[PDB]
Structures are given as C-alpha cells and as structure tokens.
Length: 177
Image (cartoon, rainbow, N blue to C red; front, side, top):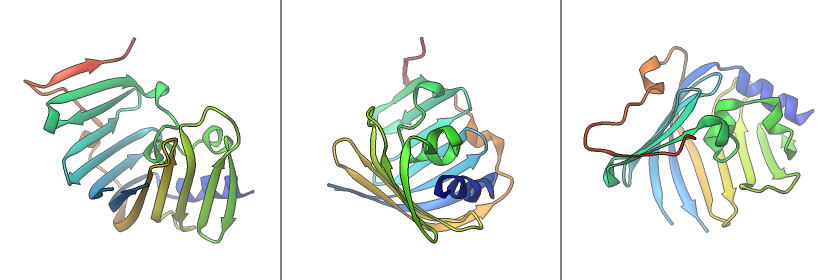
C-alpha cells in the first residue's frame, strides 16, 4: 500500500546530507542542514535566522540552542513521532501505521488516525530514488513548517555529526529519568 511504498522510498537511502529552506506559518523563514544515518541517527542544524542543533545518537535526543546557552537531553524513545525529522530518521512501519495516507506519485499526505496528536498533518514529496524534495508538518497549534530541498547528497556521512557533548559554560537540562 501507500505506507509500504513510502517506507520503501526512504529506505532507498541509508545515509544522507540534505539542505532545506524552511518556512514557518499559521511566521519565520529559515535554512538548515539535515544529516541522517539509518536507523535513528540524525542531526538537524539550523543556520538562519538564529542557530540551533537537534541531534540523535540513537539513544539520546539533544537540543542545543547556543543563543540561549542551553542544551536539553531527552530519551530518544520519548520523542519519536514529535517532529518530521523523527519520522524521516526512523522510517519505521510502526510510525507510518499511525496515519491515514494518501498518495499520488511522489506526493504523500498523512493525517492522524488516532488521538494522541502531536502532529496534525505530515506531507512529503520523495522520489522512488529516495530524494526528499519537500516535506511539511502541521502541529497541534496549527503552526505549519514547510521544507524545500536545496541539495541532497547520499552516502557516507561523518559519524561525528551524530554525537553531542554539552560544551563548557552551557546550561544543561537533562530530562532523562
């Protein structure tokens, strides 16, 4: 079905680096770099307007905001399904099963089946070749974030992109129980 097709498209590329333009609405315009290594490893690094890093090492999700001198740690397992980055990085049958999916060609639109709703909609344009040309998510507050591919490069990424150590002078909020 559409869910198995979507999963197959994302599985075509096991590791990648892709830059995206971001537009947030309901309103900011930004840019960032996305690194993914399957399974579970990712780094979303915003450069504009202000700078931030969201990094998964497969166990811990770190959010680093240098502008507020803060870094937050959560268990990755407690975050799954909260961002489009999570969805793309995991690409698990378990995740896609929670949405009703409509497909036409490379376009997929996903609407929540049931009721713990952190994401009200997710969309993605991804080729059979695994190139992610576009994606978007609508949150519970109806805020939409849309991402347009600038460049994607598939293959070996430096493993260091999936590491994080809280730097000196940075305030850590470690929420891992």
